[PDB]
Image 1 (cartoon, rainbow over the protein chains, first blue to last red):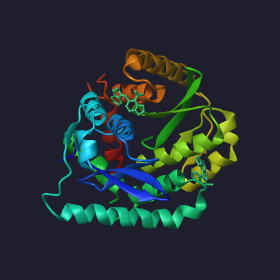
Image 2: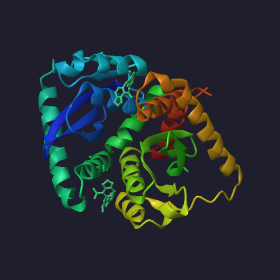
Image 3: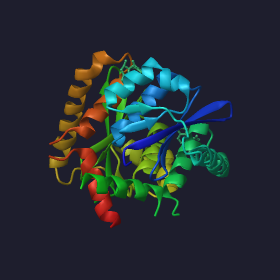
Image 4: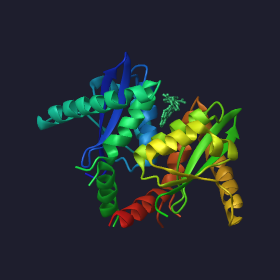
Length: 148
Length: 149
Ligand SMILES: O=C(O)c1c(/C=C2\c3ccccc3C[C@H]2O)ccc2c1OCO2
Ligand SMILES: O=C(O)c1c(/C=C2\c3ccccc3C[C@H]2O)ccc2c1OCO2
């Protein structure tokens, strides 16, 4: 549970926002890319697993599940790559709701930055710091409890 | 102390590696950029502060200390921007030693990736997971969780 993350890909301004959500906390990291390829998804997972103890990733679609580049980065970083099937259906709606929330945040900061990637990082910041404890607090508590 | 980070810039293959080190743990994040500008450093700090509770950053040089874009991102993200002067001089050597270790890791993985940026992220990974026995990644999470609680 502390090591489980979900990939999610959403579209804005003709670009792709790739998101990794730490399932137990709601904590996110995200990046803007021109389009979702295995190459970009593999690089993004390497960055994520170098920063947090990523044990399991539920991939966002069958192309990234299949991708031999994604499989190679999962092997390299010690990550169990799984499918993203919402066997519990509440998962479908939870990701949908996060994409809407994120885009709503993005629209609240959009005029403060020239480039989409900056507005996405401001949104990552606002999402992780929002008290609901924040997601950022929750992930650190979860993983610290796991270490002890 | 849990909120204090140090910026560090080093050079490799004609490119720049920008590093933020969490001083109490030794945990790092890093990126490759074509050259260190206020613009890149501001964007890097925004990314960092969206991911960890960054309270204070000791900037790596007076150009980033002065940069109005860097000051704007520090204001936006709630970060206290400070100079990076090694008032304890053991700081000068500690950062040098980190750049040499990092570059050594980079040379141990370099042939596994076409692009420098990938080898740098593999080095970030190996550095944060190295048990020295707790790893830096363990240390930063323990420090911050202690601080929340
Ligand atoms: O070769 C690259 O630099 C490269 C690669 C390649 C690999 C890679 C990347 C991550 C983890 C292990 C590995 C094993 C390795 O094959 C993949 C995506 C990228 C890359 O550049 C940006 O997106
Ligand atoms: O305008 C951008 O998108 C942009 C900016 C601009 C700002 C910015 C960036 C971070 C935090 C607050 C702010 C306030 C804001 O002025 C700066 C660097 C960049 C950018 O693009 C990538 O590197």
